[PDB]
Image (cartoon, coloured by chain):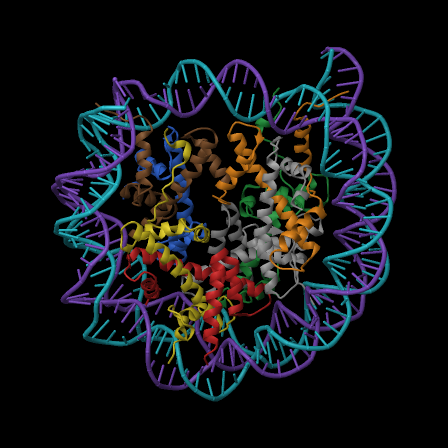
Chain colours: A yellow, B brown, C blue, D red, F green, H orange, I purple, J cyan
DNA sequence: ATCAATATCCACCTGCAGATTCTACCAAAAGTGTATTTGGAAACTGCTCCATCAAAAGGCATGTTCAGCGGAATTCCGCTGAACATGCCTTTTGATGGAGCAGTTTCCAAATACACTTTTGGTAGAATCTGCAGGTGGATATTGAT
DNA sequence: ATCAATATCCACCTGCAGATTCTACCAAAAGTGTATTTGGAAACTGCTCCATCAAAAGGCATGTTCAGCGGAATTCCGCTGAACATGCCTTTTGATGGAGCAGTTTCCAAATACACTTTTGGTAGAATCTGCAGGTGGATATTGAT
């Protein structure tokens, strides 16, 4: 039997997602495409960030992603920074940044 | 004896702190403060170690994020020393009052 | 027990400096530290009020990290990392 | 139980960066992320459906949803990936 | 077709407070928007509350706690009053 | 009706109908529509009172948006409950920074 | 068009805002913002429009927009 | 010939406008600006006049409230004349930007 | 202190846009009465993790001295915005075809609902494994005195 | 511009905790397959209400003048940062008793599902109506030149 996920060509569980859509009433009914498309976006978004993070780690000669990395990947990316502009990543610190005038001469 | 000019260490300290992620507030003390404040509301309460932690990550995260806006205000006033009125303009604008 | 008192002074001047640094702040007034503690107290007050409410609606006596999380999300300070 | 998206993340993790690992915390944070994003699109969807006296949420709402929530390139790509996945699924049985 | 609205109930509540006061049209609209807003807001948090607790029913319980979470101090106070009060009157 | 039983001017029946039809939860207690009815009406009078005043203290007997704005932005609590809301045709409270006043 | 949003106009606004003195540069700044505002809002309303398979944007479409922009507005729909 | 000193009329304009509610921008010019910004997301559209009013009521409001946090920023800098830098400063803190 | 050019009020007036009162209208609520169903409170308790106590230890808070340089205050100029009278370009006000917003009937593709079958992924947890924290010496800066 | 006092940068080395690798078990899941229901797209049809033409209204662009605000420069008092000494208390490793969270079987008070039936709130076409905004006056206060 072909899990809808494979039928859809995804790694994220389409079954889980359609399921959650239900036990969390967002609407009366839920079309079979709905979860497919959603798990799709979810998978895309997470890949996008893991990419950026993976690299973060690489730059810090680290081979395991930690929070900071996730923080870096997010704040350095104009578009993911606005998507999480109100989200706070525990243990992520802040981007090194010192205002001009403060520097010595 | 040798000594650094005023401003030199502070900077070393920003480069440092902006580079790490460990919490900055003593742990045990904070916990207490949370337990006090909670008690004003309820009593005979308990706390998941992690709940206290979640609260710390948030508080520092908020205070840190705040000082930046503050530090901007000061600068906007041709200053480099954050004063209460900077912390206040920030919140007045931020919309926290 | 121990009449928990004045713990808002547990937030040392040092600590409030360390935070200002990560905040990218070079020089600090003498009045900041207290003003700061003032700001901190309110922050917790609002977050704990809400948090404890959820804890009470659940008929529990132990404040779960989840409580703090919903409490946080409610005020638009969403936190990732603690079972959110 | 108390499910998570951990394995699914890990797979994708292994897809993009083959020799890189993730710390239990970082995963905590990715899980939060996922759930969070899930909850919003669904939300936006839910309302969008109501506003239009529609009782069903179809891939159609989930789409507009994504266009309303995500910015610039992220949405443009998201939409793609989403439409893609659907049709591929739609054309099989 | 038809378009419901709280307007009618608003007017009622008006004269029980200012027997001799009229209300602008644009004004009545704003009063409506107001109502719907608040409605959606309480209804909303209440929804969440239930879900959090793996419950499947929104009850006065939720509406209340909800109201505590949504409304400002004193305001929240009376709000709960009128609240429990209407439910007492209704049951008995 | 349930509204008269609850001694409320607000439509308990309708509030009930909107709750279920608002996909908020699977089921819905019978006291919830009542309670919420109760609190909707309550806040409703609270504004009307102040705004009614506003009309009076303006020498007018007809409430317009201005009055509603003047009633919310002048009350500490209501203003906080609507800090993110905009009332069409309401203007602002008369306010001018001290320093901007003509030095005497 | 944008220039259609005149100085006297922007003048008045700042007045209601309580402003006494106004730098000449303030105008080209104001407009740029006024534009950024409308773009973000109009964008979301039109999206709500397309979705309803409609060729005219309805006040509700706007209100809904404003709503998710965190700029709720009363007077044009519940 | 009698003149009014710098700031006196302005000051009474502050008074005038905080009393009224009237929209301060000319309808048409505005409407025109709306459609145009809009015509970049879809085309051959139409607008309920009622939707243009919302949009205008809304923007004016925002701007006004913005000129408030800005005028505060100017004063914070011990001035009385609002400048871009002040608008920028507010918007930056408002998180509306960075 | 003295006018005098003007802006701001107050009291009264009247037309008219727009709130209000009249009544038939009736679909769609809202309420009632019956029958069935199920969410979750109660009672028993298995067991996780919270409050707590002991205790050794050094990271880090506290408190002082000493002076570098930042904030505040004062002065002063030129340069930019405010006030204003002037000429008219255009936004605002009102009349009339027509394009989409909707009200309504239609019917089928699709989403329940439900009895079964089976592949999955939390996980209790014994064994195995491995990136990196934290100690350490040493070569390359970065500062601040002269 | 030489320089010694220090913090920084770094590639090594490696013990320990936290990440990885599983045999072992499965209750909750996700899939399969008719059976049964219907949400809403699709097409035809007004009837609003919106884009557009056009005329008499009334706010903006423009320039000359100078009042007064912002920015530069100069000055100095003492606030606030760096370095140092003393020692308190937070952190770190264990461990114990028992609060209270969470899991399970149980069964009834309240919620759901029609079916029926009386009722009320939303047009709407028609009429009637009135709070108040414009609009004249002339009384008086504010502002500004002297």
Q: Nearer the viewer, residue H14 or I146?
A: I146
Q: Nearer the viewer, residue D37 or J132?
A: D37
For residue I107, side relative to residue J94 (left or right): right
Instruction: Answer whether residue A23 is visible to the viewer in this image.
Output: yes
Q: Nearer the viewer, residue B39 or H21?
A: H21
Query: Residue J44 appears at what percent x and percent y?
Result: 73, 77
Residue lying at 55% horizontally and 45% vertically, measured from the top left:
F83
Q: How many marks?
A: 0
For residue H66, side relative to residue C82 (left or right): right
The answer to whether B59 is drawn above or below residue I128 in the figure is: above
Q: Quadrant of the N terminus of chain A?
A: bottom left
Q: Quadrant of the C terminus of chain A?
A: top left
Q: Quadrant of residue J89?
A: top left
Query: Residue B28 appears at what percent x and percent y?
Result: 27, 43
Q: Quadrant of residue J50?
A: bottom right
Query: Residue A43 appears at what percent x and percent y?
Result: 40, 64
Instruction: Answer whether residue F52 is visible to the viewer in this image.
Output: no
For residue A42, side relative to residue A67 (left or right): right
Q: Nearer the viewer, residue J103 or A50?
A: A50
Query: Residue J51 appears at what percent x and percent y?
Result: 73, 57
For residue J82, side relative to residue H69 (left or right): left
């Amino acid at each position: 039997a072909k899990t809808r996920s494979s039928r859809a060509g995804l790694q994220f569980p389409v079954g889980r997602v359609h399921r959650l859509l239900r036990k969390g009433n967002y609407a009366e009914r839920v079309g079979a495409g709905a979860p497919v498309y959603l798990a799709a976006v979810l998978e895309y978004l997470t890949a996008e960030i893991l990419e950026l993070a993976g690299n973060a780690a690489r730059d810090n000669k680290k081979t395991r992603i930690i929070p900071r990395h996730l923080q870096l990947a997010v704040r350095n990316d104009e578009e993911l920074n606005k998507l999480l502009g109100r989200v706070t990543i525990a243990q992520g610190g802040v981007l090194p940044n010192i205002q001009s005038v403060l520097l010595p001469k | 004896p040798h000594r650094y000019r005023p401003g030199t260490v502070a900077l070393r300290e920003i480069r440092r702190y902006q580079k790490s992620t460990e919490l900055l507030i003593r742990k045990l003390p904070f916990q207490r403060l949370v337990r006090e404040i909670a008690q004003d509301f309820k009593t005979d309460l308990r706390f998941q170690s992690s709940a206290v932690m979640a609260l710390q990550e948030a508080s520092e995260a908020y205070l840190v994020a705040l000082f930046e806006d503050t530090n901007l205000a000061a600068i906007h006033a041709k200053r480099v020393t954050i004063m209460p009125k900077d912390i206040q303009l920030a919140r007045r604008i931020r919309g926290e009052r | 027990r121990k009449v928990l008192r004045d713990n808002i002074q547990g937030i040392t001047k040092p600590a409030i400096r360390r935070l200002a640094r990560r905040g990218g702040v070079k020089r600090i007034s003498g009045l900041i530290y207290e003003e700061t503690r003032g700001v901190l107290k309110v922050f917790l007050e609002n977050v704990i009020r809400d948090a404890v409410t959820y804890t009470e609606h659940a008929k529990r006596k132990t404040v779960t990290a989840m409580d703090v999380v919903y409490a946080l999300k409610r005020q638009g300070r969403t936190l990732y990392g603690f079972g959110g | 139980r108390k499910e998570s998206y951990a394995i699914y993340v890990y797979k994708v993790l292994k897809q993009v960066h083959p020799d890189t690992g993730i710390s239990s915390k970082a995963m905590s944070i990715m899980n939060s992320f996922v759930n969070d994003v899930f909850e919003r699109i669904a939300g936006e969807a839910s309302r969008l459906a109501h506003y239009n006296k529609r009782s069903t949420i179809t891939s159609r709402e989930i789409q507009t949803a994504v266009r309303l929530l995500l910015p610039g390139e992220l949405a443009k790509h998201a939409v793609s990936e989403g439409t893609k996945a659907v049709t591929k699924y739609t054309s099989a049985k």
